[PDB]
Image 1 (cartoon, one colour):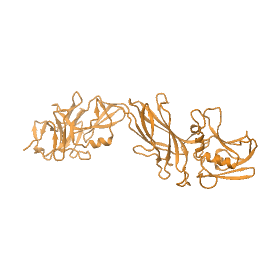
Image 2 (tube, rainbow, N blue to C red; image 1 turned 180 degrees about the horizontal axis):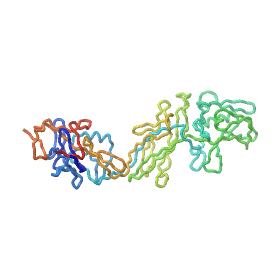
Image 3 (cartoon, rainbow, N blue to C red; image 1 turned 180 degrees about the vertical axis):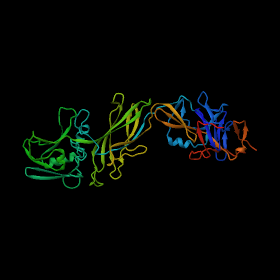
Image 4 (cartoon, one colour; image 1 turned 90 degrees about the vertical axis):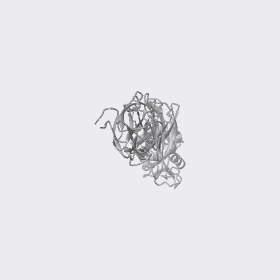
Length: 472
């Protein structure tokens, strides 16, 4: 027979509901016996209801015994981890269940964030001014010097692709030179960074390789490279190769005096950005943002001795208030690397200040995925794991066929809070009847000792609980 009530249920199979007269009572069931406080009764009547304080009770006022997870404090649920829930859910100590009606979900402050992100070097680009300029629009000299020229793209978004076009032919008037992209410590006239190329170009020719603004009164304009003659006595120079073609720095017998300069097209840098919802003690949402700039590419011809073998990105992280789209924070910079074989990220967790609270932020994995620089996948946020939770209102309640009782809330959180006690016996005839409602154990323990209704997995062994049905 179906039923309407929130805690009406029916048990199929062998076994008994467990009840008792004392709220704050408990019963422990062991393989040999068992211990107790006051009396306990057994019943197959499942027409349970809540008294004024949200305790499950029979019509005679006896409390329903089960596994109280003890997550409900003060009409509010207090979150726990599903792993430890499941192991307490096969425990052996039963007590009265208390699930009040007006139940809110207390929010949790985010103190721990781990993201899994894949960073693909050929997805998104930004003008390099985003990384090479500081907040005041001034050039960060050392970022320019240490940027791998293969970790770049031109104004039409073509990767410079130093890896497959390594040769740069430069001439002065005549006189020829060959520079080659690769490990700066290997071979002859090899370069990898903009600094390495600047130094090589300065020694062999007279010319300066400079970073300049395309519009020098602009705060943050597109930036260019510039081949300049510092002396006022002129110099005629040629230049070619794939890297030159890509940058628009091709020359033949072009003359550079002090005023005259050969300038590239505007320069871009591989880019990405991620964002995680985080919550303060009140449950208000803030936005943990990260922007990624690629600084070094993994050249396949590099050996384990190469100092810049690993692909790296520099990550700028901060927290923004979504309500005024403004950081609460100064940015925290962290340098991130990738294993050249396995494509797993290599990085160290960082400490952000979240409105006076310390939040540990890890860029390199979440609960179920690791961060990577996989070429076949787009740049992508895989998973954000985090302990913070938003405010929620009670939504609905589920009671599985195993008696496990979970509560759903408005924030989309579903956590178990209890399970219905079930006990079996090898001889139910050995129990004493005290009316049609209840049975009880007795001596001569006659029905045998009570058998905990569920196995070590937490699966009921002899039956199933049916929510919103009743018996006979």
